[PDB]
Image (cartoon, rainbow, N blue to C red):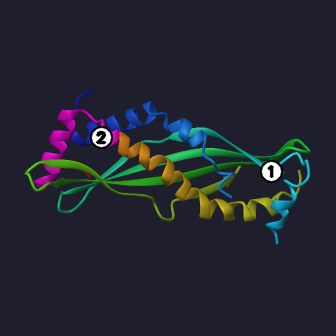
Amino acid sequence: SPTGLAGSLTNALSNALLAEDLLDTLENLPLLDILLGGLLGKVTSVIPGLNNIIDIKVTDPQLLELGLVQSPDGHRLYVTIPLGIKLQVNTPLVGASLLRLAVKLDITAEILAVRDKQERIHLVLGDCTHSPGSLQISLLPLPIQGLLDSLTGILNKVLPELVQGNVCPLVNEVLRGLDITLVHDIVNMLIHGLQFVIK
């Protein structure tokens, strides 16, 4: 089980994210709510209608194995966080299954060490974004295509930033809380541009 920094880093990050309930965060995404044609929305709220009429359940929260890359100059790290969820598109009113979807996405987190004016070194989360072009949607009686088009269209434009804004704060929290010695050895080796991530 004991190993060098890179391996300790990815295991420590994985455990910590899960222990901060990453999988509840994913499960609880306000996917629906953050959302003519647009008059229709105003209509169904003026009538005692059963709402919305559409509902989306997020299930099957999944964190996959972290990946890790160190920059050429050895000063910076990039952690890839591969995430997976299932979306179940239901209509309450008829009360039936419309769609089940698998979605997969990557967060990239940029880790660097930087030295303040008083010779101290800090572990800093630099960038933290959805990885462009990493979104993947996959369909798991009725013609249903209608949905699956302005639904993968919505998801394309809405899901990355929602996940990013939900998962990156967690990533920030897990960095601050790493083992003190694992932090100190990692900042010491990035700041002196010494390679340790092997591949």
Q: How many marks?
A: 2
Query: Residue 98: which numbered mark, if any?
Result: none
Query: Image quadrant for the N terminus?
Result: top left
First in sequence: mark 1 or mark 2?
1
Left or right, residue 147 beside residue 121: right
Dot 1 lies on which element?
A: loop
Query: Residue 54: which numbered mark, if any?
Result: 1
Query: Residue 176: which numbered mark, if any?
Result: 2
Q: In this orientation, which residue lies closer to the viewer: 178 or 194?
A: 178
Q: What amino acid type should be assigned to the residue bearing mark 1?
A: Ile
- First to last magenta residue range: 174-192
- x 42%, y 37%: residue: 17
Residue 153 at what x, y percent from top left? 68, 65
Q: Where is 121 relative to 150, above or below?
A: above
Q: What amino acid type should be assigned to the residue bearing mark 2?
A: Arg
Q: Where is 194 relative to 174, above or below?
A: below
Dominant SS type (magenta): helix
